[PDB]
Image 1 (cartoon, one colour):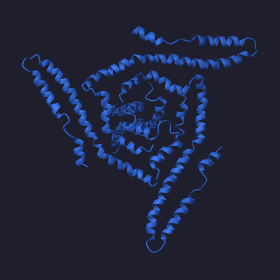
Image 2: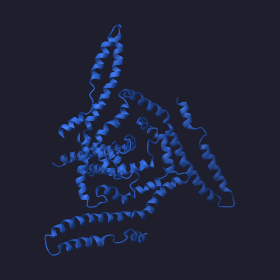
Image 3: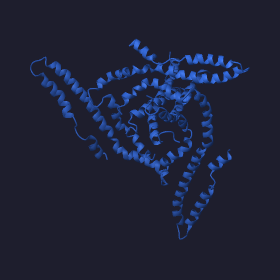
Image 4: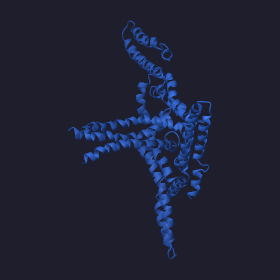
Length: 158
Length: 158
Length: 158
């Protein structure tokens, strides 16, 4: 019975995913070795030095983590909370992006609707253009709401 | 519980590969955090902004999506056909690369065979090497044509 | 049935991780799409030029793969193995770094331990500060920089 042998094989496939993490460096090699901006480098001989990166690897990881002024490394565990906390103050910009961004969207559809609907509204040609443009333009145009909302929302809490 | 509990255990183990996709985002951070060139940058404190990157995040993906205006977003639908139509016609240069590339080893192979065959060919007071050399030039050279399929195809594919 | 259809599904999940590699080419586009370092212009049509990359692939790959002079294409496979062997001797930088890596860790422990232990030691009138600094300082100071490990081992091991 090989099915059971195949059953654990199902689990091995899970192991395969962890294998992928090394591929991430291969992409970096590809990045330097294949150019820069879209494809539309002789150095690949040197890019093989990526393998040698194992020697170099203490430098990128320890530099921030422990940093030259040793004794700080125990202090760094406390700084990571501070780095997130310090930047999180500005993180509210989330509310910022949808109010401004969504606002422009209302604007282009407004232009498309006013053109098509106004044209169809004329029909007889008396004064339909007045009611169609004023009503649609009144709701979208007046819907304008300046920024500073996040500032007030943040200030009220702290 | 055992096999049934173990079966779902397989998909639970399978679940991580979707989690793994963030590593693609990590590679971006890696490029900056790894000193740019292969692993053979203090700014990671700055990379901490990536947590806050959510604020930045709706602008880069959407900018390409809607362009510098939601009116232009209407334009994106037209250019999308444009990019594919434009690149579909000139894109055939793919064949040109692989056509030349196939040809690349074909040249290396006959040249190597000539060195070995030409030298062993004489094996007496006779000009046997003249025979292996003439066959090399006539067969390889005549195996192709002066006409470029890349150019002819672009002019005959409308 | 059901479980069997679902059993092979894991095998599809294995395919799913293989699917993920394509993201690496996307990451190239994303690097450009992210402005520069993560996310914290009109060129989105230029990122589309990645599709044009099929024609481009001849230029990055041909020079690296076949090089300028011919007969190099077989040479590319041999040199790749050759640089690993050549650079392997230099690969020993693996150990020089771990020695320095653990060495600084001794440093954070040395100043941290002496500061706390020596501070509490003054409570005793005799000369405790002498024994506290001398013992900690003796192990780190004397062990600091023992000798050239990589030079001696690399020179003997070629």
